View 1 (cartoon, helix red, strand yellow):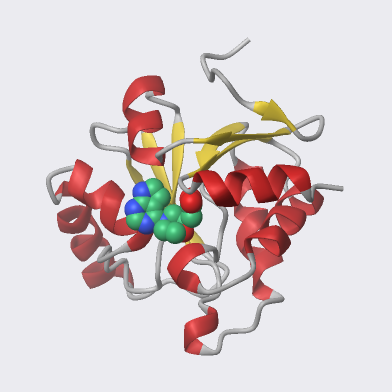
View 2 (cartoon, rainbow, N blue to C red):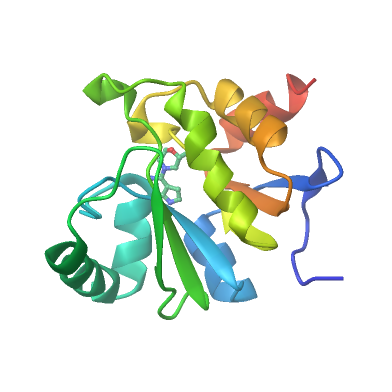
Length: 167
Ligand SMILES: O=C(O)C[C@@H]1CN(c2ncnc3[nH]ccc23)CCO1
């Protein structure tokens, strides 16, 4: 039993809710919140901008030190950093950004990072300003992630479309 509330069950291990991931993280304080990161960990907008703003820019400060030491992530890759006031840990995962021409096949590699964590609160990778089709993102999630994932979808209209079209 866990503290996630109000989710629709899509499969054995995938759950979905119309929610603001920032507000959901603040309420649940999950072990892991996933950030929709880029390779530079520049958290300017979308989910990343919202999560970083909620940490009062502490996420960005920590991320800048990470990059200065380690260099950029790979598209499809991830790193574990602090969750600050939102979660124990933040798993920064880089899905491909269609608006940069990155290969959508890398979306499966991106979701594979979730399998290193037993339970996660996450957004749909490569959705929103990353330019991929969220219906496709949900399908890849369900077909790739085997650990327990709680998906937060900000947009109510999109949430309803994702549920209604789910096979
Ligand atoms: O979850 C969605 O509905 C789609 C994502 C969410 N993206 C966000 N952008 C800025 N702030 C945010 N807070 C929470 C989500 C979020 C934008 C669109 O793609």
